[PDB]
Image (cartoon, coloured by chain):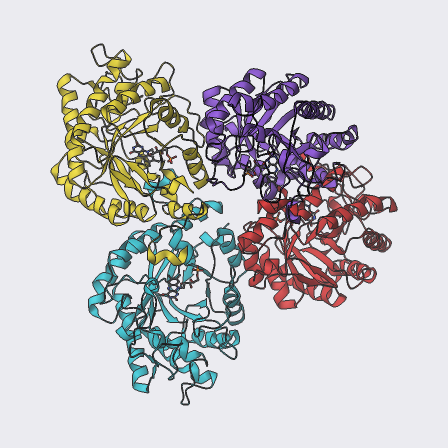
Chain colours: A cyan, B red, C purple, D yellow
Amino acid sequence: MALLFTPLELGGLRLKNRLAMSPMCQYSATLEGEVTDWHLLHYPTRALGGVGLILVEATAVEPLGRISPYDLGIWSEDHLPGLKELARRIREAGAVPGIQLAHAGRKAGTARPWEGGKPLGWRVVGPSPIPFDEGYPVPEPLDEAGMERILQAFVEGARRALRAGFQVIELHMAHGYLLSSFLSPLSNQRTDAYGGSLENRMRFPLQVAQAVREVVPRELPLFVRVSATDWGEGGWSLEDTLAFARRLKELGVDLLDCSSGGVVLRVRIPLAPGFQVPFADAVRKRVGLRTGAVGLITTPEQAETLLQAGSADLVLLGRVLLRDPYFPLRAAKALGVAPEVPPQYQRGF
Amino acid sequence: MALLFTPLELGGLRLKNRLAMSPMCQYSATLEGEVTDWHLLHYPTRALGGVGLILVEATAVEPLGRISPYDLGIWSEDHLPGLKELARRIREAGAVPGIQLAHAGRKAGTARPWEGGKPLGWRVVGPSPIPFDEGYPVPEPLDEAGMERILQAFVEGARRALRAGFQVIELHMAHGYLLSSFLSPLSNQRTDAYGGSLENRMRFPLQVAQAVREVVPRELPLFVRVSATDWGEGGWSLEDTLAFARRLKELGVDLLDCSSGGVVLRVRIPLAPGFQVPFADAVRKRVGLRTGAVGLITTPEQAETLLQAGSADLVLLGRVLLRDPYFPLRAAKALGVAPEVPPQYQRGF
Amino acid sequence: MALLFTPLELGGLRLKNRLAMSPMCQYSATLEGEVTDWHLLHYPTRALGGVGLILVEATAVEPLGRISPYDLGIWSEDHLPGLKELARRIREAGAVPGIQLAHAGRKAGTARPWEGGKPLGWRVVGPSPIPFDEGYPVPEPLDEAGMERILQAFVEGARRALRAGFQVIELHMAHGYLLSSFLSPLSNQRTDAYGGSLENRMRFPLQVAQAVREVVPRELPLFVRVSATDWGEGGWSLEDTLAFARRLKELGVDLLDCSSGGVVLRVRIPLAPGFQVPFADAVRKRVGLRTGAVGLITTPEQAETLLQAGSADLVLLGRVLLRDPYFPLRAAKALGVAPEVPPQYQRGF
Amino acid sequence: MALLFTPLELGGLRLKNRLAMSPMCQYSATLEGEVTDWHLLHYPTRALGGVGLILVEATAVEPLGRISPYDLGIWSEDHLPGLKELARRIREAGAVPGIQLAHAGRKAGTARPWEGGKPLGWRVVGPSPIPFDEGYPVPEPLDEAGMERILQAFVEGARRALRAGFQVIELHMAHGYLLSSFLSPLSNQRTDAYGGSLENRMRFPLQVAQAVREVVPRELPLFVRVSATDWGEGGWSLEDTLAFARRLKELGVDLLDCSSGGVVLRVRIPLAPGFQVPFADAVRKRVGLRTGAVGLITTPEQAETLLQAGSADLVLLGRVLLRDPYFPLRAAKALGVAPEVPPQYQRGF
Ligand SMILES: Cc1cc2nc3c(=O)[nH]c(=O)nc-3n(C[C@H](O)[C@H](O)[C@H](O)COP(=O)(O)O)c2cc1C
Ligand SMILES: Cc1cc2nc3c(=O)[nH]c(=O)nc-3n(C[C@H](O)[C@H](O)[C@H](O)COP(=O)(O)O)c2cc1C
Ligand SMILES: Cc1cc2nc3c(=O)[nH]c(=O)nc-3n(C[C@H](O)[C@H](O)[C@H](O)COP(=O)(O)O)c2cc1C
Ligand SMILES: Cc1cc2nc3c(=O)[nH]c(=O)nc-3n(C[C@H](O)[C@H](O)[C@H](O)COP(=O)(O)O)c2cc1C
């Protein structure tokens, strides 16, 4: 009896446990956005490490939607060989391969975090002409053709992702990037049908979700990651998230990946173990939409407990899998579950 | 920001953190129910260990309500000097002293667990003439005068506890003992006003809660511990617990301590970390009564997460404090919280 | 097969395991040096925690030999009732009671560490008129009658300790206190028979060891604690410790407790797990005298390994038992050894 | 101050820390002994995991010297491309690549451990016609031409290893395989110059060591792994190991890797944390030959402690790196050492 290691039915899939690798940018792609040797070592290692699902890092649906010049990309058919080999190796190592589709919006074009992370001066786009912070380029507000172009890029990115062998698609609608910035009034001050009211701010994000859902068969889960709150005064709140989650549920979205923050910088975030679990909890229990919990989950007993409480269906792990890629194998034993480990390693367990 | 070590306002008290020592029978009293040297070492150790609240083990309100011949008792003024010294030493070591008033019902009169735990053949009482299991005496069904006698014993037990300096009173209405056995239909098959319907099965337990609430001033929390489910087919369920909780809330009970099981033996209990947290979560969120979570909570991150999720207001620890009495001190440091340790020990932290 | 939990024959005793509580000043005695309620809780807690031996903190053989005005003392028959109760409670909780006899020398008369730790200006004594550091009183150099007086105080302290029921006696000859300061040339610049050469600097410490050995029966181990090095240029070194150890062995000392430092302040101490184990290892293997290892031992595997290596016969734990008094109970389980825990606690293991 | 993470000078190299990956057969080579995708994921993962040195698994110097049909081989120039890519990837991931050269001797030709491990009936060779156990083929005793052939195979294997880019060579002279079986009298009952006396039994093993040393430049360390004891009555003992180690030292061997057992089955091995550390300790301190310690080392504090004690120069880790490949990165932090982690992972530390 450990829910953490009990299969999870999502869409038409059965994940072998409730542990997923959270998407984590590695900033190690080529300038063309191609998979490199780094990702082919990085991701299969965690697959052997025991997660039932790996969500590959934010992958830009167009070059202007990248965070860094070394982000993975999926805007071109020439990304398919590298991406396909990535999903193959993840699957061969025992995990279901998924990928997060993303568009950095007004936060596009920054240096690698360990190279300063400074803006590069790209012609970034967003809902309204408001820069992210000091020194960031002023985003060019999108017109209806621009939004349609990016929507089609998300659609083609999903089609490409499926051709590559990925079986879970997450739309990155969080952390102050393009679609997250349309939701929040701190970054969306538009006066047309796509800003102002809650219904208007959700309009373009829900169009993208609907369009992608239509090209992803029901058997393959479609995730949506959101910042359940932007932690800003008068900004996007949990009640807004619940309203947004109800609409995603009606469109056929399979699971809401509940993160927070990122819309603006100078806001206090009450960091603590499980500090975003209440967001996954509220959505799941008040809307009826499956949720993924993420945020300072580092312990087997902690992960099992939030599942026991009904706060989420899926536990996503980020930083603990950077420093302990085999955490799932050893977590099973910690919970009294015989770990399914590679035969080459059975003598180590 | 670690909710686990943020003070908790309960009634007129401020507990210095959200950690409590769960009531744990020691089977080390005298034959007259007196505090001994064992308790005077056992409990202060855990108060120095850093819990904000210590719930002293099940203390019998009448001799026939004891589990073992070596249970703590509170049926006599003769118990007051030892209980007063116990509360003084707990408080001297930094924790708020509390105590669980109990009546073992049809499970009364068994040997110490490490001495066979076999029934002793007492003239035990219960709701219905049904033995707990093979070899147990058949309970004598209580009449209305008998229930009133035990109710008054709970009232006098509470008054005595307060004179002794205890500031939190918990009523043991869980684990198949007297009041638990009235709640569950597996043990209560009465056809009068105190069995059959849910309202009838709650009647005597609620009468006790109200009578005790009347003699416990508002500043001092009144807890009630319940088996949120008995895990038996057609037995006491979470929905029943919610109904029971709404009635306790109206009576002025401060907090529901959510355990499970113990009513009958041959039931499958899905043990796992936090497996009883969903019961505290449901009561808290759907009734609005504060709850205490307990059951295989062993880790600081796990305990912090369930508080961040809103599943409980208080985390109760049992077995982890038997093997690791200073867990709270080291748990603070693990959460980035400067521990408030005895000056004699600062060099160890 | 876990040497850590294999009995240890010392003198006429059998310690039930190779774990001991290292002596740790509590600064909680009365102004007359009496045992208080603090010690009576502090020490039995660790005996229940599973150590086979408890060495009670440095206990001053004369008022002027105290570190603080709140040190334990043993210079009076008036100390016997409290010390006897301390040993009884330690033994009642399963551990052999031992005690460290001490004389603070030129570091005598300082405030409690959490009360500034500043010197109080006592008429302290030492080998040479050299203050420990800025602000400390200049020690009055002892004459032969003065050393004989302190030697007799150590003898009467040992006799008193034995009457109180202590079964292991350790002589504190480390950490810059009186006898340590005679050993080290950084504190001892005498030109008579008790300074200069190594033989001269060992003379008074060895006289004390021999005098105490004479009044401690062979069945009860006599320990000596030493700073195996003072970490100062041209100071007391490991080779000196080996010479000192050979002399202690010939006198009948049972075990050398190998610490370091404390003679002067401005020295670089290479702190790291097990950093003093090489000193216990060298003494044990090159002199053949049993040794106790101490210093940043915090883990069962670490403690078991140094015993498997033959670096020591006894593992002494200090600060880890301040924050985790039940470490030995949980350490047994971690080494595949069924722990022998109080029956009241079996359900926690 | 953590010796575990202080550079180690060996031969002409400087390893960046004192942690090495012990050689661990993966049984995942082709039937031709070629490196496969498994090793190219398995080994670089541990290199990123932080070890300063990786000793690649037992690699057979001739097909008959293999343990399984899926062992790595080095008997052919066609092994060089795969082996060279393996060492390149290890080095690119930050670790020095080394390789263990081996000959299974009378234990050659067994199935994979997770496929029964049963003998296959190969024409195995050994010192004397004594089978390993029931069902094992009777080894054909080597003649002087056969020993010379295997010696030359070790020499050519070393030359090939160096051509491939390996900078540390270990000769596998332990665990009852060919050269280990020449040392022990349980398996060597020869009546010529290569059995009987200690000098005779060491003869062929020392010829191999000398021959390999001559083709490995002094700048590149040459290790020799031995079973310091066979745990058998009248068998190879620690005193024999010391005599053998003195001769290896005079030949120019850089480090003795101290294991145990494997010569025969039915012997009791006192398994415990650090149980082979006393062998590395005795060799290092009584012979003056650098040693590697291995055997149930799982903890940073444990590893640091045996280095502090002078029991070994190098800590080798086996099974802990199968279940926790990034142990070295997290061990550094546990010891107060800023870990050198890949920039992509800095946010996880
Ligand atoms: C290096 C790094 C890269 C990340 N990249 C992404 C990303 O591309 N998309 C995303 O939604 N979240 C990203 N995150 C956030 C994590 O996915 C996760 O939501 C967050 O770090 C909290 O989870 P954790 O505490 O387990 O790490 C990243 C985090 C880190 C540390
Ligand atoms: C030895 C022992 C005695 C206990 N005594 C009581 C008790 O007297 N009253 C009660 O309500 N629960 C009692 N319990 C149950 C615990 O208080 C707690 O609810 C349960 O053990 C689950 O919490 P845990 O996993 O942290 O131990 C006892 C448990 C143990 C192991
Ligand atoms: C509060 C405290 C009091 C101590 N008192 C003594 C003492 O009275 N006599 C002594 O020889 N060592 C004393 N020590 C040193 C310890 O006994 C022990 O040798 C040292 O702390 C290193 O061991 P550890 O790392 O396990 O704590 C004391 C240490 C502390 C932290
Ligand atoms: C799967 C496995 C394969 C091993 N292969 C080898 C080997 O090829 N050569 C060798 O000398 N030791 C081998 N060993 C023994 C280890 O290298 C190591 O000496 C031993 O397991 C004790 O170290 P540990 O407790 O850290 O695992 C192997 C051990 C395991 C579990």
Q: Residue B86, relative to residue C341: is it above or below?
A: below
The total number of labels drawn is: 0
Spot occupied by residue C22 in the image (x, y as percentages of width and height): 59, 34
Spot occupied by residue C274 in the image (x, y as percentages of width and height): 48, 36
Q: Is residue C336 left or right of residue B248?
A: left
* Residue A51 visible from this viewpoint: no
Quadrant of the drawing holding the N terminus of chain D: top left
Q: Is residue D12 left or right of residue D50?
A: left
* Residue A252 visible from this viewpoint: yes
Q: Residue C2, relative to residue A243: is it above or below?
A: above
Task: Give residue A204's quadrant in the image.
Answer: bottom left
Q: Residue D124, relative to residue A41: is it above or below?
A: above
Task: Give residue D235's quadrant in the image.
Answer: top left
Q: Nearer the viewer, residue C341 or D27?
A: C341
Q: Nearer the viewer, residue D89 or C56?
A: C56
Q: Is residue D132 left or right of residue B30?
A: left
Spot occupied by residue A17 in the image (x, y as percentages of width and height): 42, 54
Spot occupied by residue D264 in the image (x, y as percentages of width and height): 33, 21
At a point 32% along the width and 61% down the height, the residue shown is A26
At a point 41% along the width and 26% down the height, the residue shown is D278
Q: Residue furthest front?
A: C191
Q: Residue furthest top?
A: D191
Q: Is residue C290 left or right of residue D204?
A: right
Quadrant of the drawing holding the C terminus of chain D: bottom left
Q: Nearer the viewer, residue C60 or C29?
A: C60
Q: Residue A57, relative to residue A177: is it above or below?
A: above
